Structure formats: C-alpha cells, structure tokens
Image (cartoon, helix red, strand yellow):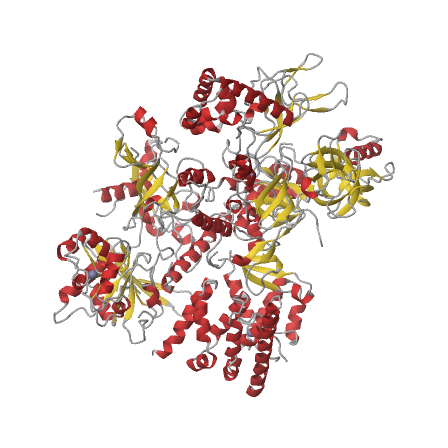
Amino acid sequence: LEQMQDELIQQLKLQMEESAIRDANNIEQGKPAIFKLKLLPKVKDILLRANLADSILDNNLLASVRLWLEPLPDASLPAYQIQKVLFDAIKSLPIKTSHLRESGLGKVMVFYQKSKRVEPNLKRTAEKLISDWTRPIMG
Amino acid sequence: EQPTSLADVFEPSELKEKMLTDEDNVIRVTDLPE
Amino acid sequence: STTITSGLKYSLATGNWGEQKKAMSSRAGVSQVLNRYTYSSTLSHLRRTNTPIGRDGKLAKPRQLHNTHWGLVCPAETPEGQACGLVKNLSLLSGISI
Amino acid sequence: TARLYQHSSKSSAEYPNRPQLAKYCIGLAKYIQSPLLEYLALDESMYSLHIHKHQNLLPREKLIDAVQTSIVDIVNLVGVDINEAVRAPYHALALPYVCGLGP
Amino acid sequence: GSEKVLIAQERSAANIVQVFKKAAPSPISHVAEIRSALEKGSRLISTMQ
Amino acid sequence: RERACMLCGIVLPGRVFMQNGCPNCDSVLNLRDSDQATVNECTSSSFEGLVAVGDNEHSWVAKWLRVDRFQPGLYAVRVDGRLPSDIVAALEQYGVYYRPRDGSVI
Amino acid sequence: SQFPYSSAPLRSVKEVQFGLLSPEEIRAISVVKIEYPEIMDESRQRPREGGLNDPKLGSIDRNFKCQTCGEGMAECPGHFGHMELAKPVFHIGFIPKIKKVCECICMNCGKLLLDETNPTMAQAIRIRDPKKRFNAVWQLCKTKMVCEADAPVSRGGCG
Amino acid sequence: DGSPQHIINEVEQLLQFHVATYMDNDIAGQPQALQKSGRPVKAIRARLKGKEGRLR
Amino acid sequence: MFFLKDLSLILTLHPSYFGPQMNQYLREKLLTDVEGTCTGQFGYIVTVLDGMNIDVGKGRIIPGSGSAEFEVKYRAVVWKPFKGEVVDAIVSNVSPIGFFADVGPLNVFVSTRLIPDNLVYNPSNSPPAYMSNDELITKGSKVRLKVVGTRTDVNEIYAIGSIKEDFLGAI
Amino acid sequence: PQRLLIPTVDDPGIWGVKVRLGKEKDVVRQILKKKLAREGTKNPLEIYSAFQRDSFKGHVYIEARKAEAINDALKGNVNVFSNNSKFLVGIVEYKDLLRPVKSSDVKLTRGSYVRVKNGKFKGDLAQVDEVLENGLEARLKLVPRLDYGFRPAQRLFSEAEARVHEPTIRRDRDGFVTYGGEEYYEGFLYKTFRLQNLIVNSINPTLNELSLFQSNEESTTIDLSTIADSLKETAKNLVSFQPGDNVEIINGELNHLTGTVSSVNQSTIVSVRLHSDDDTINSETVEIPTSDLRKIFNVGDHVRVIHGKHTDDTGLIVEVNGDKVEFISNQTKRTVIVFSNYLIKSTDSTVSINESGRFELHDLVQVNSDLVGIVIRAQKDSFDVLCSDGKLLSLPPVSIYSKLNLNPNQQIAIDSNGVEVKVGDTVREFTGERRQGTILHVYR
Amino acid sequence: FGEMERDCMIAHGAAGFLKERLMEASDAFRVHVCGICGLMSVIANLKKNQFECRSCKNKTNIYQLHIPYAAKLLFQELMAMNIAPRLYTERSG
Ligand SMILES: [Zn+2]
Ligand SMILES: [Zn+2]
Ligand SMILES: [Zn+2]
Ligand SMILES: [Zn+2]
C-alpha cells in the first residue's frame, strides 16, 4: 500500500529527473523545453493528492522539485506554469525543517525572492513561505 | 536587465518631418544647391 | 437654534413625524394641508382622527363601526376606499380629556 | 491669405485669446505690410490658391515645381536679411527659397 | 405660508392588562400584555408579556 | 512645527532641535552645536509614520526600528532625506555605522 | 417610414436565447474602459474621457452626436463600456447556485463526486431538462461527502 | 503598496458589498445601501419588479 | 477565380405593380440589381444563368405595409480573388508609387516595395514604365502577379499584387 | 542586523483599534503623554509602543501584552469609538505594518523631464534641474510664458524684447538674468515648484519640446539615457493583447516560439496555444506573462495604428523590418513606416471622422476662389471633395476656404418647366441617363 | 393602455390593433442586431452606410428590428447584470 505509493513516487522522481535532463539538453541543442510541460499534468495530479504527501516526504521528491525550480545554466527561468504548480504544491504540503534539510529548497526559495524576473505574486508567496519555514527554528 | 539611435526614439515620419535623417545630413554636408 | 426650528418646521410641513434623516419608518400623514373648499369642509377637517393601522395586514374588525362608538364618533361620516372606517370624525358634542 | 490665416493653427498659437475676425484682420494687415511673407506663410495651402484657369490640368509635381521656381525667382530678386531672419522666424520663412540654399 | 392641520392619532391605552388568545399553530395559547408609561410625559417606556 | 532627527529617528519641533539638540544623537551629531543647515541635514520635517514608544528595552518595535537604545518619545517610520556625505564620513570616523531610515535602503 | 433608411434587411425576432456574459464577450462588445471616478473633467463641459460620462458611451444631448456611431440622440442606442475589477466578486443573484455547484463537485480535482457507474446517477443524467437534471444530480451528490481518488481503478478524483 | 490582511479583507468586502447592492438592494439579512437623502438606493432589480416596474 | 454559386435575394414589391406582368418585372428587377454588383462576401457577380426562367415563389404580404416580399433563388457566376493566388493581368497605369493593373473588374495596385529592384521606374520613357535590361512593363503590358492582400469596402474590393517572386513580372 | 529582528511567539502582541478619522496622531500623542505621566507611579501604563500609518486610515496600532493594558491606554479618550473595535494583529503582519513605502525611486532624479500639474505652465514639460532635500518642492527648468506687457504661449525669454517692452530688467550673473522677479538662466526659466505641482510618471514627451530643450545642449536630444528609459516604458505599457493574436516569446525556456492568444485573464497572464510541427504540442495551452510576448505581424493583414501621429490609420502590411513594420495606408493610400508596437491587427477599419476638422459629410464647401465642391468622404488627415465640374480632389482641412452657409433665400432651384424645387425634393433627369434622386445642395 | 385592456384586445382577436397601439402609438424604435452573436452591439452608421460588430468581426450578417424602446431598455439593463439576451431572426429546433 504505502510501499506501492513509494515505488510510484520514486518512478515519478526518475521520470522528472530524466525530463529535466532532456529539456536541458534540448535547450543546449537549440530546442525549447517541452518535456517538463509534457510531464506537468501527471506531476500536478500526483501532488494535488493529499494522502500521498507522506510518501512524497519519505521519498524526498522535493529534491527533484528543486532541480526543476533550479534555473538552467543559460540564465533562463522555468516556465511560469511549472513555477505556479510547484508553488501551489509547496503550499499544499506540510513542509518541515527536516524536509528542507533533505532537499535544500531554501536556497532556491531565496533566489526566487531576490530575483526580479519572478512574478511579484510569486515573490510575495516566496517571502511568506520563507517566513513560515523560519518560524519553527526560532520558536 | 541593463542595456540612442534616433530611429527607435521617434516615428520615421516625424523624424523626416523634423529633418533628422541620413539624407538630411548628406544634403547639409553636400556642396550643391538643394 | 437651527436644530429645533428646522426639525419642527420639517415635521409640520411634510407630515413625517420624526427626524429628517429617519423619514422612512416614521409615521406619515400626521400634518395635512387644511381643506378650504367650503366652511363645512374646514370644520370637518379640524375634527378628524386617524387610526394608523395602515394597509398591510388589513382586517375588517378595525374598520367596523362598534357599539362603543355611540355618541363619540360620527356613524355616517367616513372616507371611501382604502381609508374607510380607519378615519373617524368626532361627534358634535364630543371632547378629549386634557 | 487672410481667409486661410483665420483658419490656420499658426494664428491660434500666435493669438490664443483672440476672435477669428481679429485673426482675419491681422492677416489683412500683414498682407498689406508684406504680401510676399504672407504668401510664404501658406506653406502647403498656397498650392490650392486659384493661380491659373487650367491650373488643375497640370500634374501636381509640375505645378509644385512651377510655384517653387516662381517663388525662388521673386525672393532672390528681393533679397533676405540674415540678421532679421535669425531674429524672427516670420522673416526667416524666405531663407529656404534663396538660390543655393534650401529648407 | 401654507395652513397645516394636525390630525389626531388614535392609539391603544397604556397601563392596562390585555389578555388575548393566540391561534392554534403556536405553543402559546393565551397572552397577557401590558405597555407601561410614566404619568409625567405620558411616554411609552417598556412592554411586558 | 515638528521635525524628525534623521539619525536616531526621534521627532521633535525644529526649534527644539535648534535650541537644545537631539537628546540621543548629541554624542555623535552635536545638533545643538550645529547650524540650521546641519539641523536640517540631520532633522527633517518631512516624514511619515508617527511612533510612540513607552519601553525601549522590551518593545519589539523599538528593536525592529533600532531605537531601543534611545529616549522614548515621538519617532517616525520613514524620514525624507538622507545624511550628507561629509556627515556620513564624520560618523564613520567615530566608528558608528549609519543605516538610513528613508526606506529606499533595506 | 418614420425611421431613416438603413440598408440592413428588416426581420422579426423568432427566438430569444438567454445565458451569461463571458468576460471575453464583455471586453469585446465594450467601446471604452472606465477607470476615473470623476464624472466631470474640470466642471467646464466636455466630460472626462475614460470616466463614467465618456462621450463614446453615447449622447443624450440634442446638439451633441455620439462619437462612436455618429448618430443623433434620437437614433443612438447607447454603447457599453467595461470596468475591470481588481478582485473577482460574487454575483448576488447566483450565490445559492454557486453554493449548490460547490456541493456537487470536488474543490480540488474539479470533478463530480458521482459517476455513471451508479444506476441512479445514470438515470438522473438520462433526463433532458437542465434544471431537473441539476436538481437530481445535486440530490444524489449531496450525500457523497468525500472525493474518491479510486473507483468506488482511478476515477480521476483526488481522494 | 502594503498588505495588512485585515485592511485587505475590509476593503475587498466593501467592494463586494457595493457591487452586490448595485444590482440588488433588498438582500435580506443586512442593511440596505442608503443615499445622502436617507432613501434606499434604487438598484437595477428594483427597476424590473412591481406594478411600476419595467415589465408590468 | 470564377465559380458557380446558388444565391438567394429578398425582393420587395410595391402594391402598384400587382399586375399580370408581376413575375417578369421581378425578373428584370433582379437582373438590374444583381448583375455587376460587388459584394465583399462573394466578390463580383458577373452573370445570372437562366435569367428568364427563375422561380420566384409566392410573395408574402408584409403586415402593416402592404408590400409583398419575394424570396428569389438563382444560380450565378461569381469571381473572387484569394490571398496567395497568381493570376494574369493587364497594366492600366504607371506611377512612381507603383503601377495599377486590372484583373477583370478588379483593379490591383502594386507598390514599388513589392516590385523587383532591377525594374527601375523610367519616367522619361514614352510612356513611362518600370523597366529593366530585359524587362519593360508599361501601360497595356501583360503581367503575371500574385495577389497578397484583399481589402473589403462597402461595395468594392481592393487587392494588392506582387511580382517580386519567380515566374512573375512581365509575360 | 535586520533579518534576525523578525518577531517570535513570545514577542509582545500588537492590537489595532478603529478611531475617528484624522485623530490618529492625536491619539498617539495622548497615549504617549499618558504613559509618561503614569510612568514611575503605582499603576503605570503597562504598554510598550504605539503608532499609526498614514495609508492605514482610521487605525492605531499598539504593541502590548494584555487587553486590559489596551483598555487602560484607551480609557479617558474621546476619539475611540463606543464599541471596543480591537483586533489581534497576526504575527506575520508585524513586518508588514512597519515596512517602508514609496521606495520605487531613490527619489525624484535631477535632470529628469517631468510634467507640471498646475500653475502658469500647467502641462508644460519641465526638466528637474534641482531637487530640494525637503522633497515637497523642487527647482525646475521651464520655457517662459510672458507677454512683456488665458496665458501666452511658451517661448524662450528674450532679453532684447523684454528690455524694449520693459527696461527694468535686473542682472546678477553672466547668463543668469532676473526679469520681473523671475530668474531666467540662458533663456530658460528656473523656478521652484511644489511636489504637488508635478507628474513624475506616465510622462508623454513631444519632439518639439524636446528639441526646444536640447538645442542649448549643442545636440538634438542628447539626454538620451533617460529618453531611452522613457522609450522602454512607452513600448512596454502600450502593448495590449486580444484573443487570437499571433505572438512570439522573448525569454524563458520557451523562447523563440510562436503561438496564438486563446484567452486573456487580468492584464499580466495570457493563455497561449503554441504552434509547432508536432501535433501533440499544438493541443496544449500555456499561460505566459505578457512581459515576454512580442506580436507577430504577417504581410498582407489589415492593421490599425494604436497611437502616434498616424492614430486611427489602417492599412495592409507590406514590409516587416523587425521592430519597424511598413504598411500601405487606406486613407492617404501611401506607405507609412511605424513601429510594430503601435499596430493592432484589426480586420475592419470602420473609422469615424466625427470631432475632427471643421466640415462633416455632405458639406458644400469652397475649394478656392473659383472652385466650389461637396464632401463625399472624410479622413482623419484630409477630405474628399466632388466639385461642380464632376471631378474628385483631396485637400487638407486647412486648405479649404470655408463652408458656404446659404439661407433658403439663397439656395433656390428652378426646374426646366420653371416650377420651383426646394431642398430634399426628388427630381428626374430629363435626358441622358434619366436618373433621379433627392437634392442635397443647390449652387448656381 | 393597461394589462386588462390588452387582455380585452386579445379576447377580441385584433392583433393588428394591439401591435399598433403598443408600437406606433407609443415608443417605437429601430435597432440593429448581429446575425451571429445576436446582441445589440452593432455600431451602425447610417449616413456612411457601414455596419460592424466588433465582437464577431463581421460586416454582412446584420439585421434591423422594430422593437419598443422599453424592450431595448430592458435588454440593456439585463446586459448590465451579466445576463445576455440574444435575439435571433431564425429558428433552429
Ligand atoms: Zn537623533
Ligand atoms: Zn452612438
Ligand atoms: Zn477531488
Ligand atoms: Zn456579433
């Protein structure tokens, strides 16, 4: 049951990493990033399912989430749909300090907060999430 | 994020009306009646 | 001095018995223009009484001529239509206690 | 020239608080003072003046060239003061029509 | 400049007990009502049931 | 007429600043010992966000506004104008770092 | 014959189709965007353009012609403008229906809480009248208080 | 400019109230929108109903 | 390009014409009101086939105005240019801004920016023309052009041609 | 530091209380005075701080720990409303309540070009020579509006004309002249203006004023960095999108991709369906920010000018030179080159000429001293006139003499038989085509 | 000409008199409707002889109607409340 969900989430993790690598190569080959957009619906459907959050945190899928959120070496930001969906998923899940330590998403969150090409709404949401994640450390 | 050509500054019709084009400089420099 | 003056003048001029900004929910029609068509009409108007039961939720019993009305209100004089029975006229020897 | 001046926005900029008849009278007075400068002030509307009976039979380019040649000849026969032209643009209207020169 | 007349307004007397029979679709069968008014000023103050 | 001392953030009448100086910044500004130009360059009448502080030690707001080491009184969230370059250098000579309260620096 | 000649053919209404107005249609049929609360420009005639009395909306004065159609007061039907809302708000006439629709669907996956597998649900869908169809679907799906991420196989729900 | 949630809630609720009363000023359970004269505002819904409405 | 289309027309007849010759009169009225007209939706209607045997049906009396309304269905030849189509033409005028050609009833204007550069306009030539070393296009010269854009007017159509691609220009 | 000072759970709470409008600072001062007076007493006001913000009208925020402390602070005040309208501020809001405002620009920049809100030069473009440190006023460089003895047109202050019309000119420095109490520096007025007298955003510059300002700089438009920034702002703000527009993507992973706008939401999120050789990709809709979209204009499309000198001009695209697009006009029937930022693909023109010029349709006007005609079609830039001869002409509105206003005692028509025929009557040609129609105007 | 008079005229069966009373002897009006969207959004300019519905981007499929001015006002007030009454001159089934 839970182990089956963990296996499926690990398969999703492998698919997401492979899609990110393929899109990075395609951009390096002069082609638009399409694989991330293709995989976006399934990732959205999986993330929207609340009962799978525990298995997601068991498999540390936030590492692949950060990998997708990490800007590519061409200094090009990811597609706005991907950013919006990932922000909504991050809001929808109970992220703890241990999960952040495993994933290290705080660095990308700070980068998004400091950046200006990022949408101002995403900027405000990043500030809110960073404050919420700093809340437990100080009390 | 960080970056003069008068062609981009104003419409070419307005520039030609105000006499700020390359033909204008050539005519002014040229030693001939217009 | 304008407060009392304007309040009294407005209530007497328009007939709305209340404050000017609370015209709704106030009892209207208290003050009316004196009827001067003929002498009898003026005399009748100066001795007129009103029952503020209104039109909503009407019933026949308030409009009826009751036994106890004998000698105090006119059995014959009443308007037609909506206000029939609700508007009464004092009898010719009646008075109101002070 | 007075009729055309009473409708030109040049008068409106020059006289923002004056009636149209005042502009017409000013145009008449300026025409009396100097017909050549008033004819120059027409700019493009000078080509719509009734010059010849069959003025419309000629192509627009030929009529424009004829007007340009006539006005250049007349202004060169007259002569233009450079200092006054610098002092006032109204007197500087005649500067482009001098021989050798141009707009 | 206009002549206005005050029409006398009829109201139920105060300081008297009125007993009424309520209709069937109600848990209440009979009601005793009284409205109070001070003698000085003859102004309505409160109602009790 | 009231002005906001740029350095400490306190707000007092400009004539009070001229006659007596800033009770907190006098150790580094010498506002009383300064002319009207220096008073204006360190106290500005154009400001926003009047703040009244009762207990500097325990008020989190005072720590957030860095006024927990100053005299309680009228303070401004934002003050129009910054310290001049010469006054900035003079304060840096004393070893004190100046953080603008103009809001444009954060 | 009391109307000025128009080359468009003259026909009579045969059907009235109702419905709601999409924001795209509201923006399309509009002729100006209303943004300035001031009714009058400077209280010197010529009401402010982009305000609530823009001349493009139509003319109600005899000597003023509409700036959009060019017709007189007797012929101008009036033209609509649109106002963009900073935050979406409820339509006061549809709040009960909005509540019912929220009860009928899942708030996360955006799908119906019941499917055609249920014989009663299929029977309800079989009906034709939209109002009675919605009433039956609401009567059924009201009881269903949990979204199913799996078939009661995945039905598309989020659980 | 700046977003205290309490202020945002208050102002957005005011906007919702104004838009709602612009189309229906007889919403049971809350006070009506009033003019400076004290009379209630004649909403669009009130234009269409009654003997004196549009249809009748 | 020419086509055959089945079109319909609404014809209103005044009561003063309610005579035995009603049908023939409707026929000539249709012919006069359709032959040669230009509609942006269809293009140009050039002729009506079987013009003397068109069915008109029964006219309906308009309530309150007496006039009868007839629905006339007919088959007609229609010509309409299309975007990106190459057709033959005859030059009608030469001008510095470009030259005007005629494709049947349609008059097409081609600007200099859509003309090959080697075809320099020669105003000294008699008549003035846009000529090159081996090409000379003047009034009355056959030209093969491709229609790029069509402009719709009330009862007129304006088309723009080009000769800048291969197999175009003089023919 | 600044980050470490963010509030914690054990930090003192913050309450907000509604008060009467305009009394917020008064309540703050009263609270401070009460705290000082009761300080050092048996029952001091147990609060920590209190403040208010100008934007958050009607609210006063007090930092304390107990509701009784708030009641004690508010006790004895008249600006507090009858009801205890107090609420607990959320801890996250603590940073926002004290965050600064108006941080968009370091501050008004000296040398920038601005517009004037009100005064003798209402609307005139002005350069910010000096910014006063107070921030309420600023010294500005303007074009003088003088008559030298309803406002005169702007014109550089001419010292010779000023002396001729008024010999009381003062001199203080070389190139700095004071005339009539007004300081003019090298022909340009220098006058301080209030911040409440300026528009520092959405500034619309004109070349004429730009040339008049930059001529003294020995180069036409050289303050070009700020000019370039203004150009960027005008290009960015003027773009408006509609469904079905063909657009191209400038940034992002999807850079250099074409697509059609499907739906528009707000003004910053646009749903786009992309076009590509792969069918599975063409069936996807992507929401893309408008800041990374550029309109795609294909040759042979009806396009209408949005803004500029050629506003409301339409035509067909002919040449696409990247940023600048060329199209043949419809009214003038001549090629016009305008930036792609000023064009919208509008398949239908339907241009209305009302509120323009002096003449409307069907106006009998006098072309010149000899030719008299009537208007057949009006344009935004000119008019089309059919004359009595039977020919067509195109002339600017200025060139036309005037409308021939004729009374019915002047506009009289007599038919062949001698019967008078008035305006609007229907007559039929006796010979020729034998046409008929309604009379529009009668002349000779 | 109230509702009871309208019912009496219906009982008599005189449809022409009723139409004339309520249109010609009262607020008669002429509007243009798009043949596609069915809304009264056509920007008609009679003197220039050009009709155009911006939403549907058509210039041809346009008809004119004779309706009471009160009906036009009612439809416009309905559109003010986000309700779209579309008038079509042909049936569909
Ligand atoms: Zn200080
Ligand atoms: Zn109109
Ligand atoms: Zn669900
Ligand atoms: Zn339509």
Vertical placement of residue I77 versus K84, above or below: above
Side (left or right) of K38 relative to J435: left
Determine the residue positioned at 68% across, 65% down: J278
- Front residue of J213/E12: it is J213
On the image, the x and y values in percent for residue A104 come to: 46, 78
- Front residue of A9/J110: it is J110
Determine the residue positioned at 52% across, 52% down: K81
The N terminus of chain G lies in quadrant:
top right
On the image, the x and y values in percent for residue J248 come to: 59, 57
**Ligand 1 quadrant assignment:** bottom left
Side (left or right) of J95 relative to J245: left
Residue furthest front in the image = B31
The C terminus of chain G lies in quadrant:
bottom right
Determine the residue positioned at 37% across, 55% down: J105
Side (left or right) of D99 relative to J135: right
- Is residue I3 in view? yes
Residue furthest top in the image = J418
Residue furthest left in the image = J41
Vertical placement of residue H37 versus A39, above or below: above
On the image, the x and y values in percent for residue J358 come to: 53, 28
On the image, the x and y values in percent for residue G103 come to: 53, 70
- Front residue of E20/G139: it is G139
- Front residue of J292/F56: it is J292
Vertical placement of residue G82 versus G40, above or below: below
Q: Quadrant of residue F30?
A: bottom left
Side (left or right) of A33 relative to G35: right
Q: Quadrant of residue E24?
A: bottom left
- Is residue E6 in view? no
